[PDB]
Image (cartoon, rainbow, N blue to C red; front, top):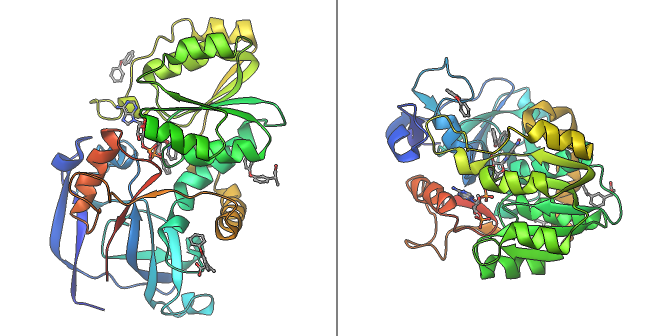
Length: 343
Ligand SMILES: NC(=O)c1ccc[n+]([C@@H]2O[C@H](COP(=O)([O-])OP(=O)(O)OC[C@H]3O[C@@H](n4cnc5c(N)ncnc54)[C@H](OP(=O)(O)O)[C@@H]3O)[C@@H](O)[C@H]2O)c1
Ligand SMILES: C[C@@H](C(=O)O)c1cccc(Oc2ccccc2)c1
Ligand SMILES: C[C@@H](C(=O)O)c1cccc(Oc2ccccc2)c1
């Protein structure tokens, strides 16, 4: 329980993470209320939308300064009396809540997830795993022999959309930007990995899947979204999970050729369905429970990229978050990008 700590703070609204966010060095350690845990963060998750958050896009009325980081895993170092009925000092806990980019974060006990130990694999589940699980269960209409296309398939959430679709006996196609990532996809049971830098995705889908794909787990936006719509089967479902190709722009939007979208959907009786995890929190506990079971049992690969093969090596310390965000946006990661705060 130190007097002071470091944390990241959004000091200016911008999708340029380095220009928006400051490493603040002499911050008091916040104290937990009656219903709160104080978590010493050991690993924190880097998420594409960290730059949407720094840009102010979740609530454009809220001015800087504000905390940042959506998820953490670590040890309970202090807690309020009511919280102590369910949690104990020293316990491993994980959470999805704002302000994880800090050495210590106050988290309401009611939203914390107990975990068996502090491993970065368990953090991969909190946002990336639950997003894939809930969207596909609630909106995917998966069943044996459906064809599922997953974009950013070798990324944090993509790896789960791939594996969970396979567990539903689907035939799965996955896009990624390298042969190393394609090999990773194959190792997860991907039926058709596509390196979109060396193989034209539109041609692959037209030639190999002429009747189309039944479900798209679409994270990329832009030209990839356009191709995905064209590739939809009759009654197919494209799920808008995100559009990372656009987040760095002033609006966060990626250009699409969507003027003909209503016509295309009518012609195919097909759909475009958005998904925002925070609209489905009633499903979160059950998703996390099943994901954790599969993770511990070794029935789910939870790939972690701690940056050990990045230019400057392992993502250690809050200062490495800047590098880690850049790494994501250079498309370099395989699995979930995680930063370690060692102690
Ligand atoms: N709807 C929700 O509630 C929700 C929740 C969590 C995440 N998401 C979304 O899921 C997506 C993935 O997020 P993540 O945090 O798991 O990241 P991630 O997939 O681990 O990393 C992003 C990957 O996207 C590709 N990429 C990066 N920059 C790109 C660009 N400029 N243009 C095109 N492709 C680019 C790269 O893979 P390739 O090798 O394939 O290029 C990169 O590895 C994002 O759209 C995010 O907003 C949505
Ligand atoms: C119980 C069964 C089932 O509900 O089909 C199952 C087994 C293994 C992983 C699952 O997780 C998911 C979750 C979403 C989509 C596909 C599979 C779901
Ligand atoms: C009970 C659990 C724990 O203490 O975290 C455990 C015990 C032994 C080996 C494990 O191996 C792993 C490690 C990472 C993810 C899944 C399984 C995980």
